[PDB]
Length: 114
Image (cartoon, rainbow, N blue to C red; front, side):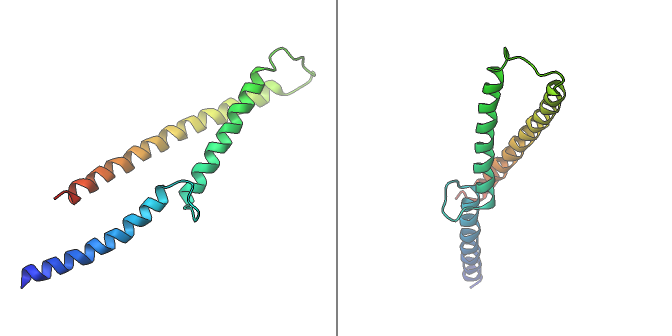
């Protein structure tokens, strides 16, 4: 009868896990209709970076164009390289956070293995 109790408790847990992990899939998915917060962040980030990359290429094309002294281009360029450096480190950190997510995912797998 205790073996019957254990199996009943497991089904309750397995049913609740199903709900939670369905929610996780939604969180990690992209392009969904009713999208998660992470999806919105993912899509906006990648579109913003596309713009930055485009603007960077345009900037490089402006190497020969003359100046309007006085113009704070060197000052504004300094602030830009600063912000990009900081975003670079943040992107590296977030990638490392993703690796942590992956590590827990694999830990989750070993529990679910028969």
